[PDB]
RNA sequence: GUUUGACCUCAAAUCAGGUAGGAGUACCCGCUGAAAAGCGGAGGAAAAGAAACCAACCGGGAUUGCCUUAGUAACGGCGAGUGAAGCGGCAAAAGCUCAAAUUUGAAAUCUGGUACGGUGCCCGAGUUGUAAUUUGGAGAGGGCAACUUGUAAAGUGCCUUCGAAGAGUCGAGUUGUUUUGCAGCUCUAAGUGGGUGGUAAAUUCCAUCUAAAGCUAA
């Protein structure tokens, strides 16, 4: 038996989190990380993100999320 | 007193420091006449009081009393709707042809999502000013929200035209100033 | 070359001080915080690609008793997996001396490391790992800091010494080979020394013998 | 006392040993043709977090429940 | 397949002899004389004593 | 229901909006005493998932503590102050470099609403008096480290 | 510093509601 | 409209009704703590208690106590000596309640007062949510079928559509303490997620639960 918490992400959930992150804005370390990306590349962006964080998987997750932000913002 | 000092000191520091643009969407609110006609519209759709409810209940129970009772079928009631989780519930259907959101709520985080929610959903939301007056039109002390879904044919045209009006007065006027940081000027 | 030292979530203080001492040994090595996954290993290459290191070390601490290590070149084929045994830390009086951290290391092989090709690979890649270029800080003074390797039967005893004539100064390694596989961290398994037996198999043998005894009883 | 499942033991020392358990399952009591909630009022133990994984244990405890149902007379 | 990928790794080994004794190494011909009862660490330390003294002579010379 | 939106908006605390609310409410409480009453919970979702109900017999106190555990000590403060009330549970709301701010839910076993409504009559038993004193609260059990 | 907030995701409008809850019986019959 | 009124907040009551202390403290629960004392809090028991469990099996199935596991594993100038736990036999056995989606075709909820625990009437509390229903063992909506127990409540077969959960938290660095846990400061996530544990014929597999909320006799 697999708990229904295991199944997947509902549409309501992705909607909700997108709406939250829209209304929240970007934190000063995130406001930093966007400029560090745009300036000195994803390598240094990942380095700074991992230094801010503890592990590396959260670092790649953060960098991928922020690249999604950058792409969906600049082009649209 | 301590609390008079606090409440006079409150609303000074908030304007002293930069409020986030998600706030100051509040207090950029509906103008005089338009709120006035909104409330005139609503006063036809007051909900039944507990007292009126009990009068009709005893009336109909007495109607069942007779031997020689009377049995009939009656249409749906019509009234605004006002409970917060219920108000959000009528959203995400959608059913709210109008939603009014009071600006002054001490836990403002109860309401910060509602403007953006109805914006993305296309519900014609409006920021009314004063939760107490919403309470007056709903047989409550305060409501903080006022949603309406079902409207009689005798007001449907009025509802649609008021919807276009609020779209003209709120969505057009203040969207670009909803779109900036407010406050930040010292007091 | 530049080097990285990586550890796993398994932690024992006597086990931890070993990594600190090793980091003190190599200046070009780094002490990046420990990784979450003991199973995913390819990402480490990216870390090396992010840190510009030609050889990367990963220490796996399973169950807080079992110690394995990988040392591998991150864009590059050689990968060798080792088992670790019989360790001693800086606290006790075996050692009785310290060194300026960063002198150029001398090294020694108490074994041919020529006839056996896989041992020759272990030999050369160890030379890579512990080869210190001039960029190492505090390399101007020579502290007579030296290391040696010694296959006893198949276990490399790895040791460190300073002059007094000599006194031992650094961690005591009884290390065992496990296997060799291709690629940076993945590429297919090529060689395996069958003489090695993991302690999991040992506890399994003990438990199986106990079960057989109970069944006979 | 409340009637209990005869259950198989874990481990290898007593892999051959059979024991008295806590409760059967929802699935087994359904196979008895009765509900767990009503089966409580009759004095049958029930365990939800347990899973039936052996056929013979299941069948034996089913027949055990049949004979329990047979020997009981219930007052209205 | 063993020796072939082992030669592959030998090629992947970037250890040139351009710089002599910069790795600073002395390699031994024979193994340590380790009797199982004898304290084999002490059987070691005398031989590595010998070889490090040899390396010190080599470094002082060149 | 809207309480989800409260939960996930609370999830992003260091965001601009909630940090602003943190920074205004910390000051506004700073003008107030160490201990005082709140009319309504400032985090109603947290209060509900900790067991809050909006009716007579549920008291909200806001407690200020200098930087045992800080949450447990904060609970004990109201435990001594409101002896008649029984401490249900607390939660974090706000903080400062000088003080941390917590919101505690207390329940009166004397109000007939609590004495009736058998959902909550259990707290009326004398054995539950001063749970915070014996570490029987959430933070009490966590600090004691009682789990499986 | 400060910068205005981008509205890159609000401008997209969904044409459907989030959840497909089946309508209950009681909303159409006298209570 | 310089008026008046909606709220919110705060005071004041010789206003109504209740509630805390203190003694004792054999047992119990927390804090502190030396070479135990002390502090705080009950009760007839208390605590704990229905798995973010134990295991690797042919799997077990809340908690609690006794025998065994056992002076074993593990720890320890591996010295003094310290010192468990799975499982098994036994006693006694008990399971439940929230928080997540709307009743919106009618807050259906409840304190208090008053006239006769109940009933009526009236103030109030409450939509910034009291009731009913649902706690993953699913559950909800309806329709059909029969049953079983005033267009009353509940149980089962089938079709279709839906089917919502604990964040200054998890985790990471560092400091102090402890034998891994705990406490502080900087930082802080994710949802076919997360935690824990095995596993390679390794660009691995499958294994097991669902924390950050709560009650519960023996």
Image: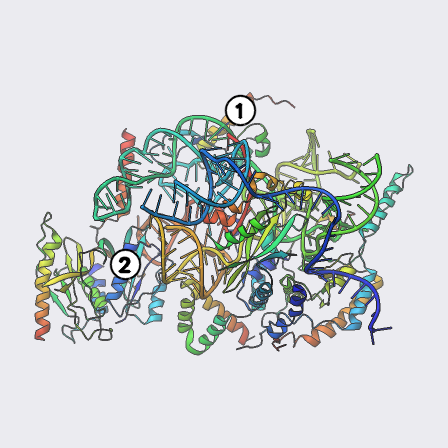
Please give the chain letter of the residue carrying mark 1: D
Could you say which is closer to the camera, residue A56 or residue E2?
A: A56
Frontmost of labels 2 and 1 is 2
Residue A32 position within the rendered picture, expressed as x and y whole percent measured from the top left: 47, 74
Q: Residue at x 33, y 54 (%)?
A: C10
Q: Residue at x 54, y 45 (%)?
A: F131
Residue D3 position within the rendered picture, expressed as x and y whole percent measured from the top left: 51, 27
Q: Residue at x 20, y 71 (%)?
A: C103
- Is residue C181 among the parts visible in the rendering? no
Badge number at residue C17: 2
Circle 2 residues within 10 Å: few <14, some 14–19, many ≥20:
some
Could you say which is closer to the camera, residue B166 or residue B52?
A: B52
The colour scheme used to paint the residues is rainbow
Please give the chain letter of the residue carrying mark 2: C
B118 relative position to H4: left or right: left
Query: Which quadrant would the N terminus of chain B be assigned to in this image?
Result: bottom right
């Amino acid at each position: 038996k697999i708990s229904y918490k295991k199944g997947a992400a509902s549409n309501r959930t992705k909607f909700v989190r997108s709406l939250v992150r829209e209304i929240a804005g970007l934190s000063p370390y995130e406001r930093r990380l966007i400029d560090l990306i745009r300036n000195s590349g994803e390598k240094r962006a990942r380095k700074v993100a991992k230094k801010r964080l503890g592990s590396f998987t959260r670092a790649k997750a953060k960098v991928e999320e922020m690249n999604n932000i950058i792409a969906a913002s600049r082009r649209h | 007193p301590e609390y008079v000092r606090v409440q006079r000191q409150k609303k000074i520091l908030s304007i002293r420091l930069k409020v986030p643009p998600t706030i100051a969407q509040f207090q950029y609110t509906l103008d005089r006449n338009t709120a006035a006609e909104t409330f005139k519209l609503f006063n036809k759709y007051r909900p039944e009081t507990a007292a009126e409810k009990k009068e009709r209940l005893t009336k109909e129970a007495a109607a069942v009393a007779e031997g020689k009772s009377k049995q009939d079928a009656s249409p749906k009631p019509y009234a605004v709707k006002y409970g917060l989780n219920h108000v959000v519930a009528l959203i995400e259907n959608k059913k709210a042809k109008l939603v009014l959101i009071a600006n002054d709520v001490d836990p403002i985080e109860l309401v910060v999502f509602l403007p953006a929610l109805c914006k993305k959903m296309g519900v014609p939301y409006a920021i009314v000013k004063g939760k107490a007056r919403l309470g007056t039109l709903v047989n409550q002390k305060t409501s903080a929200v006022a949603a309406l879904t079902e409207v009689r044919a005798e007001d449907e045209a009025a509802l649609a035209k008021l919807v276009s009006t609020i779209d003209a007065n709120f969505a057009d006027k203040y969207d670009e100033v909803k779109k900036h940081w407010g406050g930040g000027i010292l007091g | 070359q530049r080097t990285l030292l990586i550890s796993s979530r398994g932690v024992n203080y006597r086990h931890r001080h070993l990594i600190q001492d090793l980091s003190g040994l190599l200046p070009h090595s780094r002490k990046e915080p420990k990784l979450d996954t003991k199973k995913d290993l390819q990402q480490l290459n990216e870390i090396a690609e992010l840190y510009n290191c030609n050889n990367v070390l990963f220490f796996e601490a399973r169950k807080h008793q079992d110690l394995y290590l990988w040392l591998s070149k991150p864009p590059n084929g050689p990968t060798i997996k080792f088992y670790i045994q019989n360790l001693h830390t800086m606290d006790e009086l075996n050692f009785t001396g310290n060194c300026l951290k960063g002198s150029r290391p001398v090294l020694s092989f108490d074994q041919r490391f020529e006839s056996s090709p896989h041992y020759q690979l272990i030999k050369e890649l160890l030379v890579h790992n512990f080869g210190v270029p001039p960029n190492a800080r505090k390399s101007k003074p020579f502290i007579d800091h030296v290391m040696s390797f010694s296959i006893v039967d198949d276990k490399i005893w790895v040791r460190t010494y300073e002059i007094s004539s000599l006194v031992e100064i650094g961690p005591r390694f009884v290390m065992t080979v496990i296997l060799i596989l291709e690629g940076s961290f993945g590429g297919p398994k090529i060689y395996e020394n069958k003489q090695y037996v993991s302690p999991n198999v040992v506890r399994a043998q003990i438990k199986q013998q106990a079960a057989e005894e109970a069944k006979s009883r | 006392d409340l009637l209990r499942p005869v259950v198989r033991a874990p481990t290898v020392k007593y892999n051959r040993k059979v024991r008295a358990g806590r409760g059967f399952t929802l699935a087994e009591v359904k196979a008895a043709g009765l509900t767990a909630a009503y089966a409580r009022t009759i004095g049958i133990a029930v365990d939800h977090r347990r899973q039936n994984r052996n056929q013979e244990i299941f069948d034996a405890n089913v027949q055990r429940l049949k004979e329990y149902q047979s020997k009981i007379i219930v007052f209205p | 397949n063993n020796t072939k990928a082992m030669k592959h790794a030998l090629e992947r080994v970037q250890l040139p002899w351009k710089k002599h004794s910069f790795q600073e190494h002395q390699s031994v011909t024979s193994e340590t004389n380790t009797d199982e009862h004898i304290k084999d660490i002490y059987d070691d330390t005398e031989r590595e004593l010998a070889f490090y003294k040899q390396s010190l002579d080599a470094v002082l010379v060149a | 229901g809207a309480y989800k939106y409260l939960e996930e908006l609370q999830r992003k605390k260091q965001s601009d909006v909630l940090r602003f609310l943190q920074r205004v409410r910390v000051w506004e409480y700073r003008q107030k005493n160490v201990i005082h009453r709140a009319a309504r919970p400032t985090r109603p979702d947290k209060a509900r998932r900790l067991g809050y109900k909006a009716k007579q017999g549920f008291v909200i106190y806001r407690v200020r503590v200098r930087r045992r555990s800080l949450r447990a000590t904060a609970e004990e403060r109201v435990g001594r102050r409101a002896a008649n009330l029984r401490v249900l549970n607390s939660y974090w709301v706000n903080q400062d470099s000088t003080y941390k701010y917590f919101e505690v839910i207390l329940v009166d076993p004397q109000h007939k609403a609590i004495r009736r409504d058998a959902r909550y009559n259990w707290i009326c038993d004398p054995v539950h008096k001063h749970r915070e004193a014996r570490g029987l609260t959430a933070t009490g059990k966590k600090s004691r480290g009682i789990n499986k | 510093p400060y910068e205005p907030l981008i509205d890159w995701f609000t401008r997209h409008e969904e044409v459907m509601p989030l959840t497909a809850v089946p309508e209950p019986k009681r909303r159409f019959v006298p209570s």
